[PDB]
Image (tube, rainbow, N blue to C red; front, side):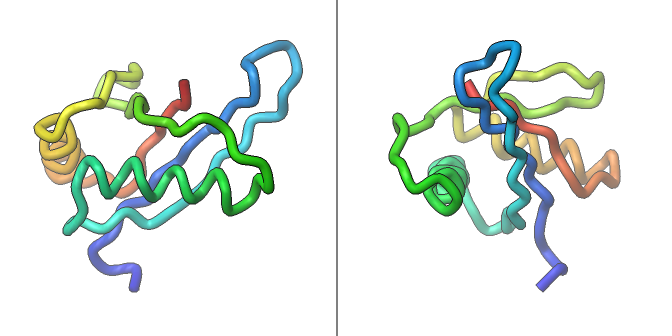
Length: 98
């Protein structure tokens, strides 16, 4: 249930312009997941709403303690991400699509 999960936000952009209407999905990312299992959940989220099939995403940036978007393409990067919200007592996270 709500226990043992993290609110992940993905501002899926169309083409990034003056008009595209960005969509932010909210999925509960478990703590027993991995970097691959994470990027996989996001992919299904894009196909869950959009009937079409865009290019498979494999690069996303998460929000750190400063508020800047840091690259996340490694396994260790995911481990630290959990330790980040752990000490910060956080619960959610802002991610950007590229």
